[PDB]
Length: 218
View: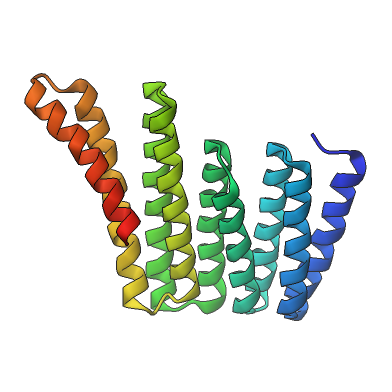
């Protein structure tokens, strides 16, 4: 929960940030989004983190209405920082869910072919991270959940770079690698538990570990 004033202070930051986004003042967007983040740290609660993510989303949505791409980058940047600072699977799902919406916001304003490609590609990264999370929770093993979280972090950052520079092919290929690796880890996890013969299970386990290192190398 949040003290009734904490909810008020965030809405104050929200309006100030939204205004800066509307007026295209990015440095003020950057500062206000910082304040929203620091509230989330001080509070340290899941519900506060979700509120900060909402502020970042509203900032991106408003900047997209006015064609201010830079303010969108600031929203995406803070979302990934919230995600990378988190250690629970709910924040990561929320974070990647917002990055999808931000990528859509980029499309509305930019409206370029690259933006269209980036949007389609971030929601596949969100879909892969979600599946990996759900599968890890089905195992009940915390260390497998730690892994799903780690991969969702990698997917989030790599989705930010796409948002920042959708034209760059290096950036775009980097996420393609991550998404594939995540999908490979999910299948391997399923096979490591479901497979009929022991040889395939062992190979699946070695496969999980191999897919993680690859995404880390990207």
